[PDB]
Amino acid sequence: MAALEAKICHQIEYYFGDFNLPRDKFLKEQIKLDEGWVPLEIMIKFNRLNRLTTDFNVIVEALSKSKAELMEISEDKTKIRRSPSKPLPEVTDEYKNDVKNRSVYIKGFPTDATLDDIKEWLEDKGQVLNIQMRRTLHKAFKGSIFVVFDSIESAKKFVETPGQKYKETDLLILFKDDY
Image 1 (cartoon, one colour):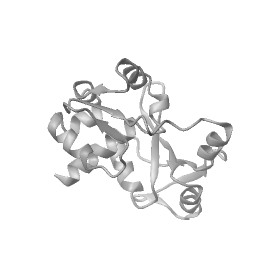
Image 2 (cartoon, rainbow, N blue to C red):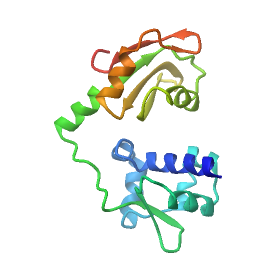
Image 3 (spheres, one colour):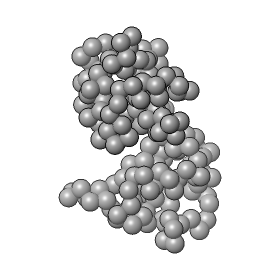
Image 4 (cartoon, rainbow, N blue to C red):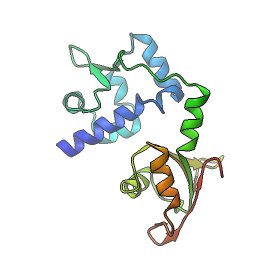
């Protein structure tokens, strides 16, 4: 259960996180409806969470044990929200350049690779805050992605690592800027 709970925590914390939330039109709209609270009945409509479970009890139990302490759970346990004490970061020019400086472009993945395959591949490449799978105008995966690491250090070590491959396939790795 712990493994599944960890997956649930990470997926929900990603939705309400610093990277996704500011760009999530639908979620931002929901957060305006009831002081940040979003019914779990709405949360289970989120594709990736839905695949893990739709059981409100399992979702709540999971979040209750999170270390991130990012989410709050309602008294009746049917709604969740990002803690109002954890406001979203000010998006200054410095903040954006900081983000850009730890973002990396990676080309070489097979077009049938899933977000899960890539997340698994990156597990031992450093803490990542976002994986942006680039797609064509017909929504097909291009084989290239943008990855936002936790620190410039993590990004640089990854980039400076020679001969990296996604199971046999040589990859082209460049800092977002260089791309």
